[PDB]
Image (cartoon, rainbow, N blue to C red):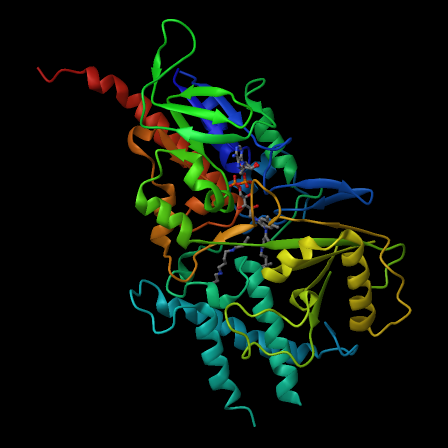
Length: 456
Ligand SMILES: C=C=CCNCCCC/N=C/C=C(\C)N1c2cc(C)c(C)cc2N(C[C@H](O)[C@H](O)[C@H](O)COP(=O)(O)OP(=O)(O)OC[C@H]2O[C@@H](n3cnc4c(N)ncnc43)[C@H](O)[C@@H]2O)c2[nH]c(=O)[nH]c(=O)c21
Ligand SMILES: C=C=CCNCCCCNCC=C=C
């Protein structure tokens, strides 16, 4: 059948290949790195497995295709410290969570608005919190410090440096549908890859440029013509009828000018520029003995009312939201520019800084140092350049639709988490986007007979 090349071997590209390979096209998946999975990345560490990318199945239910596949594949199981060194009360934490998450729910008021009074989620949250503080008759400092951690948690969830960068009106479009895969989330992508024909995926084969809108001859005689040519970094010249591009939005942001020849249509090129693509990283620390599920950290004397969209915390580690005890391993989460700064530090500097933080935060100066560290470095990953998309101030959910828009004749199709308007930044949005592109091609192929059908 037709020649199809899929660029990228994350869940979107594998999902597209799986549907297409199930009048079979001549299909190849070109992966830049040495293994598949992309932002699903599981590593054997500390005598177990650590998730460097995606960790949870969001909304583990019947409608979630990722949950459905994990069940079919047998991958599922049956199922607060202050920087002062003292405990924070659960009641006060609850009261501040009610206030904060109540305001997050109110962002729905801005849905479908062309001209919102404030451009961002962070500005709306700051204004409402400032009005609330004016109602409060040292307790005020503790309240603002706890609210600061909730802003930082919300940054991690959005994968943004600051909630002031997240567009307000589009925020409510995202659909909220949480569990892990004990043996590794990468087990899911490995199983989809295994279902494909032998040698469908080529590893260490990064694509340099996609040439489209042409009539390209194949090397063999007589020289059959194709609309697209994929140029690999290694010099391979691969003709195709269709190319499904699943590369991350961070890669497109850096390379869209050279990756397509001719350049992309203006509206799509602008969608790539306007959308957000932030960094979220994990830091795993291994201890010989546990000193301790989730330890939330509150940084004394901090407040979300001081910060602007691009302000940094006093130190990089003050952006850390807390630690998840791994089911002796702790996993810290950090997002934004402080997380990008973290990636530039040596493994030793991260291990030693966090040991000092943990000794201060638990109020135990004799706490033994972490034995080892493993951290992700998503912003530094040349083929990703960050963690996941968000609808940034200046962009809308319409920009996600523009990311999905195919090029003429379906010569070039786009899939990936940043092409799904309601499930962007998830594994299920990426998988569904791959199935969407496969369905679009199958309909084109099934329509080709109709071109030869006379009316009379
Ligand atoms: C309880 C309760 C209530 C809830 N509140 C609690 C808070 C929990 C919030 N959850 C947070 C979840 C996070 C952080 N999770 C999280 C954490 C972190 C640190 C990250 C990094 C992500 C995530 N996500 C996002 C997904 O990982 C991501 O969207 C998809 O994997 C992308 O797939 P893809 O589009 O195919 O791209 P890919 O990048 O996978 O594939 C593209 C491929 O293209 C390749 N490529 C690039 N350029 C190329 C070239 N030139 N030539 C060839 N190949 C090229 C490249 O090498 C890749 O292999 C999560 N998603 C999810 O569902 N659960 C989660 O837990 C998280
Ligand atoms: C209502 C409400 C809140 C909507 N919050 C949007 C979350 C952004 C999507 N990120 C998902 C996780 C990951 C990765």
